[PDB]
Length: 63
Length: 52
Image (cartoon, rainbow over all chains, first blue to last red):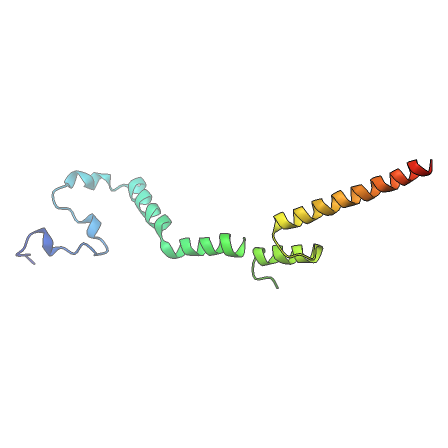
């Protein structure tokens, strides 16, 4: 379970790669409801398929 | 039966006026024909005044 290389053994594209702690343990207390909610609301707003559907609905279908 | 509001607007414009186009085209045609209609009504008034 050891990585002979350094931080390069981690996978940056993993699902929970943003939440793997290396030395920033002060951020653990910042994982409350509000901050996680804001992060995931930002992701959902940035979601691409829903945005394309919004463009199609409001620009094409609705003129 | 309309695919979208844009096509529906074009159909409305074609139904009200012969020339196809947008809402601006509809407004322009209606304004021009309103001016012509006002000119004709003033011509009727001028006929009344002239026969007077």
